[PDB]
Each structure stands twice: as structure tokens, then as C-alpha cells.
Image (tube, grey):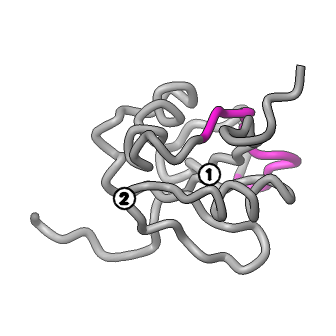
Amino acid sequence: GAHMGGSMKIRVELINGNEHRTSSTPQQPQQNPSVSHIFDGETAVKDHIKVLLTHFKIPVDKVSSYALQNPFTLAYVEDSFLTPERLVEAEKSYFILRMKPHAIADR
């Protein structure tokens, strides 16, 4: 059934053309790799991200540089935890999971 209400099964597009693995294609995706993932406000974002990464076959070590982004506003979730509001605004369409355009600091 539809997993909607509190926790949401939201389609996430993944961009990972930073690593050179695509559908053996160039950087023009018809669709991006997508998953309908269970998001909730009980699980930290990064943990949702470690899952997504893993489902997209990306090492969770990249969780650092990955963020959920809104498809319209292009706003990133830099939150540690998701809110119902984030989910709700996301169910409207999808979430995007991208490597954050930002310089990598030697943390």
C-alpha cells in the first residue's frame, strides 16, 4: 500500500556522476536513479542517507557530502534530523540526494 502519513515513502533522485558510474551513459540522465525511501523524523538524516547511499551502491563514508535537497527551492537539508514538515514538503514531489557543491574541508 501507500506508505504515507507519518513516515513517508518518498522518491529520491540520486545524483552521483561525481563517481564515474552511470548507465554507461554521459551526464544526461533521462531520470536519475531513484528510490522510494521511507523517511521519518525519528531517524537522523545521515542515517537515511547512509541507507540511500547504500541502496545506490555508494559508500556511506560519503554521507558527509550528501544531502537531501528540495526539487523546487533547491534547498538542502542540513539538518541532523528531519521534520514532518520536510517530509510533507517533499511528498509533494521527491527528494534529491546529491553530493553537496562545497569545498571539501580536511575535517
For image coordinates 85% across by 56% down, the residue present is: 93
Farthest left residue in view: 107
Q: Which mark is residue 15?
A: 1
Which image quarter is the C terminus in? bottom left
Mark 2 or mark 1: whose residue is earlier in sequence: 1
Q: Quadrant of residue 66?
A: bottom left
Residue 11: x and y, percent?
76, 42
Tally the marks. Answer: 2
Q: Choose between 19 and 84: the one closer to the eye.
A: 84
> Which amino acid, mark 1?
Ile
> Is 41 above or below relative to 73?
above
Q: Specify the segment rendered in magenta.
A: 27-39
For image coordinates 38% across by 76% down, the residue present is: 102
Per the image, label 1 sits on a secondary structure element best described as loop
Q: Which mark is residue 80?
A: 2
Q: Which mark is residue 91?
A: none
Q: Does 48 sit left or right of 73 as displayed?
A: left
> Is 28 above or below relative to 105?
above
Residue 43: x and y, percent?
43, 40
User: In 3D space, how far apart are the residues under numbered discs 2 and 1 (Cα atoms)?
Assistant: 21 Å
> Which amino acid, mark 2?
Ser
Residue 25: x and y, percent?
74, 40
Per the image, label 2 sits on a secondary structure element best described as loop
Residue 24: x and y, percent?
70, 33
Q: Quadrant of residue 35?
A: top right
